[PDB]
Image 1 (cartoon, rainbow, N blue to C red):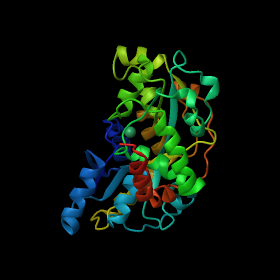
Image 2 (cartoon, rainbow, N blue to C red; image 1 turned 135 degrees about the vertical axis):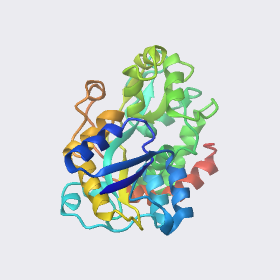
Image 3 (cartoon, rainbow, N blue to C red; image 1 turned 60 degrees about the vertical axis):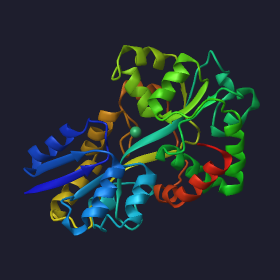
Image 4 (tube, rainbow, N blue to C red; image 1 turned 120 degrees about the horizontal axis):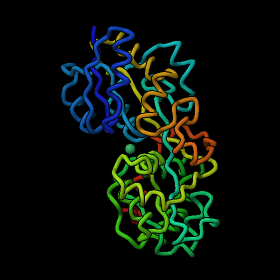
Length: 312
Ligand SMILES: [Fe+3]
């Protein structure tokens, strides 16, 4: 018996978690790890001829792309329905959350007054003029953040916040979260918005000594309440090994499985905050209760309003 996993968790960190499932169950895990959008495009092309059993994807926006494209089948599981929090799964049971990431504020306290920064709304302060730096609108992470704001405040109010935010940007858009962390730490940027786990990875020397030194210069602010995003798993629509795909998903969503995946990328497990000493130092967070499904709903409108105010 075997199971074929196509995973968009492209961090090169998760192989060990699949090995523990194999040893306990005797089910062979064939594992492909690449870009999420390459997986979606390949699967649309293959249809019934695909060898995918279980699909793992990063971000609300990519999960919505896969759902729109009809890539998942509904599954029934007492374990999953009674263990994965409602806000972090498909109401129609086609996909399930496995890890939690926060998109946070990073600041250089030698360049800006950090006592003035608590939440996203503060980044429109005119005293931050020229000092705010962003990754481009092509990042699903950024699209899902603007989608978060539309969910709570509606389109009108979100556009006001975006006109204010983009006003304070005077630097070209970055193509990644790690290069924006380097700019904030070097001090060419005073304020950035990035995923918390990139700061943890650089602090722990994963990207070498220079990136570690730059990351020490940064003060990380968790908005209160906090915007939460996820990685998720679902069973492929035409999975051959359906039974084995459900067993592996039940394992990855469990306390052992969710801690295993999360501890590799410095994320939070599903039902508890990270044990990790670097992540714990960032502080406690309270979720804002916007569902992952809602983040997918408002993705199209988020892209249109980012384009309209000039977030490029
Ligand atoms: Fe990432």
